[PDB]
Amino acid sequence: FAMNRPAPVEISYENMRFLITHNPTNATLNKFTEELKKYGVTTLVRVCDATYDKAPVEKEGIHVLDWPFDDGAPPPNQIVDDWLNLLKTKFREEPGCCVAVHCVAGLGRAPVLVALALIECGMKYEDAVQFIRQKRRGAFNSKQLLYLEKYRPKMRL
Amino acid sequence: FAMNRPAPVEISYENMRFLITHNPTNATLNKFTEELKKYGVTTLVRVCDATYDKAPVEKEGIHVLDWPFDDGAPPPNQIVDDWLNLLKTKFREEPGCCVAVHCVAGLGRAPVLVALALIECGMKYEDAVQFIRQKRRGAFNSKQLLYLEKYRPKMRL
Amino acid sequence: QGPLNMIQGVLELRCRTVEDVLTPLEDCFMLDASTVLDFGVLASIMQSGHTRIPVYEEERSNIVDMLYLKDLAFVDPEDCTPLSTITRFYNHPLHFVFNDTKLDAVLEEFKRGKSHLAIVQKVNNEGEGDPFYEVLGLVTLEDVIEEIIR
Amino acid sequence: QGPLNMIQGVLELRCRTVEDVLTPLEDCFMLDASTVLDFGVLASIMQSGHTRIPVYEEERSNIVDMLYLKDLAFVDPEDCTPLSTITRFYNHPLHFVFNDTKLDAVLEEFKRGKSHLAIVQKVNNEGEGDPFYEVLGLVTLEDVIEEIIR
Ligand SMILES: Nc1ncnc2c1ncn2[C@@H]1O[C@H](COP(=O)(O)OP(=O)(O)O)[C@@H](O)[C@H]1O
Ligand SMILES: Nc1ncnc2c1ncn2[C@@H]1O[C@H](COP(=O)(O)OP(=O)(O)O)[C@@H](O)[C@H]1O
Image 1: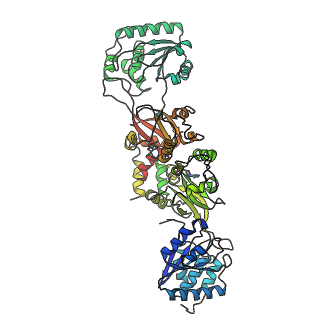
Image 2: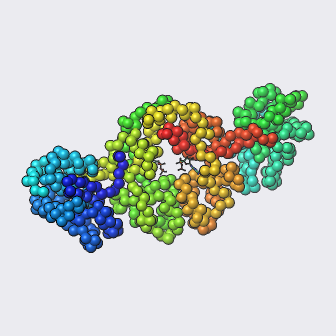
């Protein structure tokens, strides 16, 4: 405990499974995809701009999705609707697969989307943050915590 | 205190003055003589065999005397008589000069000769050893301590 | 004085945090990733008297790999071998500690583990933007000791 | 457990002696004076993970100078520069401690002084011959610490 690594993080819940990841370069692109295969991700959502070629990752058969939105903001309503619809279809395709989200800061807007998923799958807003922050300390800013509080399930997974 | 150096040692008493020294090579011969000039020695007594040339030391005007005797033995009676006669003449030549003695172990037979000098200048056998061992720990072996005990002043300095 | 002062030292390990003991970034010996290992930089390494040296690109707060002394083993000065080649010969692990962390934990983990070196993060709340971990500098075993023995 | 175990450690510094804590000669990284500094021995130095390395001629118990890491600064491997040239570029001081010496003294002197390294002597009574100081090995600051923190 109390010491850690520049390293992926996993959140599991029902048969949903999520990975939050570092940025690569092209320099360690081929190693990066091998991490992802190891967690059995079918799907990457880039929520922050990156410069690497995605097509090595896509060649090895992971669906890669470029959905960038503003630094430290809530996701716009399109992106949440997309993201929920994506999760339906991709856990329909394979139960107990993983969906990767990654940014260039692993705290912030990548875990927001995971917390959005967890809330519309069960657990309380209070509870949902706690599971995230246990795994990556200090996880959202106050605007995101606002949005995560003011958020309502349908409950559409 | 309690940490020390590969380094000369001084014993003073009346206007007698003595240096006990390490061995040099030729490699640091020229530095070695500069130590000796710094203590103002006129006289070196080699009491253990060494290989260096003495003539650099003798050129810089120190009387060098090759008086070797057996490892861990008392000095033979010639050597003591010589050594005492040397001390007379050389403190006659210059009061408050230093006489160097050196071996290849600075504990042992070099400090015996200094203790011989101190005994025939005053101080008690018990006292004489103590001044030596304070300066270089563990200074004589038992044969030498025997000889230093059984030793009698005339008192011929 | 003395041993009594030291005993208070070990007693205050539970109080005191990494923040108190660290070497801050501006006093860290580190190299740019793009550095070449010519005669002079190799000299500069071997002058620095450190065995583990952090490697950054291209802002200093962005630590990326570690260089070990052992990594330098058969390098020829002006091969001019660049740094990131040598950092790419090895996985050396890089460990991160939080600035919160009490010293007695840190000491026990150093007692356990692989490297004598962690690098130091705090979280970062002010900012409009995303939260990030902010690099403060280095803490070693010898850092934690110096609390006790002074 | 723990900090309580450490406090006994500092309390036993007055009891325990250098004899108990030292690295004995047979486990010391040292070089012969006549060694040449080619690629391999330089590699061997930088592998050894030591910054201060004793130098002997020609029995191992006869320590003569110290090599520092900083001494290696602008040497070219296969110049083949021999060791004793580099040891002759510098007075580095070499410090000697007695095997008797209690740890709390040693720790305070290390707290003071120049080198983190002393080398260890006992006197030698058995033998027919002259008394001599007998070289046992090395003690460092990190040695004395390890008493406390274990
Ligand atoms: N690469 C480095 N740059 C700057 N300071 C360092 C570095 N490595 C260690 N230190 C500092 O040096 C001190 C002692 O470090 P130590 O544990 O002896 O490792 P090293 O052998 O690298 O010096 C500590 O205060 C530590 O913060
Ligand atoms: N030249 C050397 N050869 C063998 N062991 C050494 C040497 N220098 C230090 N040590 C040992 O390594 C341990 C820690 O040494 P440390 O104080 O970290 O110095 P270094 O940075 O040289 O390792 C101690 O137990 C010490 O006895």
